[PDB]
Length: 129
Image 1: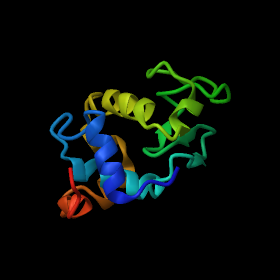
Image 2: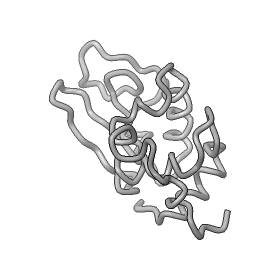
Image 3: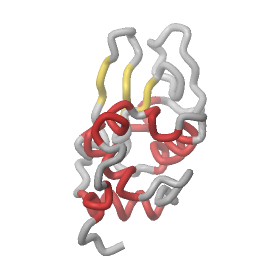
Image 4: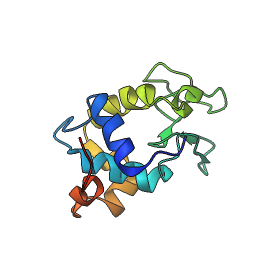
């Protein structure tokens, strides 16, 4: 599924992401924009052999099981394929764990490089929420 901007904002709010760990909804939408361009099916291989999955590009090195990342952990206790669903519940639940791990949203390199410190409210501008 490719979400619209406000559509994703609404879905994220519905699943309790808005202001989760103090990160406003615009931060989460911005992260999704630059991680996946709002595409729930996005997958990207990392040089080290792990893979990033879904709307928030969650990494099999730590967070989900894909059966092909030697050494890795599955701290969200989910198959990585669950992070590709049209329904964002699994990705949201896992993102909540990631953002609570100590470094906040810096876990998402694209968030740090492209969203952090910017006018993130623009991402929810005009949205009926």
